[PDB]
Length: 149
Length: 5
Ligand SMILES: *C/C=C(\C)CC/C=C(\C)CCC=C(C)C
Image 1 (cartoon, rainbow over the protein chains, first blue to last red):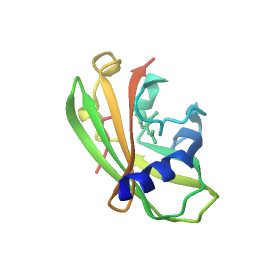
Image 2 (cartoon, chains in turn cyan, brown; image 1 turned 90 degrees about the vertical axis):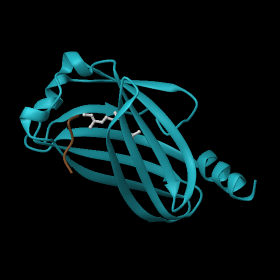
Image 3 (cartoon, rainbow over the protein chains, first blue to last red; image 1 turned 30 degrees about the vertical axis):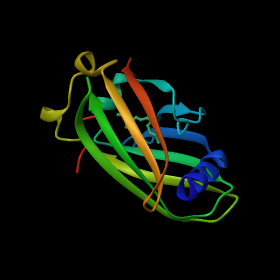
Image 4 (cartoon, helix red, strand yellow; image 1 turned 90 degrees about the horizontal axis):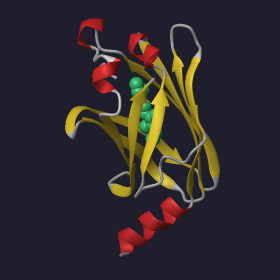
């Protein structure tokens, strides 16, 4: 429980305040959430406008609070399609000061247009699985089912 | 590494 008690302490003190997806070419926010999708043990749902599939790049912005210090806060994200892994991403934030609020921005580039999946094939069939870690320590795993509308 | 979305 030693590492498990610490993971629980971090999770209990951790909150996603807000998150945005922004078209990096226009600067326009496409999608905004205020729900804490770090919360495990529930299948979250998100509806995103299907025009996100035509973006060359999307700026992802997350604002999070952490009571607990983290040495090397990072995310692993798997994109599952009808239960099959299509892409896996790794994002590193690094040191988190205890009881800080933090904005974390990442630019996610689109595959060439010819490789992008159609909205009608994707919608309802995509799960994003996010593992939140401090270094080696798994703090939380959350799942979000994506609809393209 | 690019996304397919
Ligand atoms: C095209 C779709 C993208 C860029 C991913 C959508 C993801 C979410 C909405 C939420 C998943 C991420 C976190 C919980 C940080």
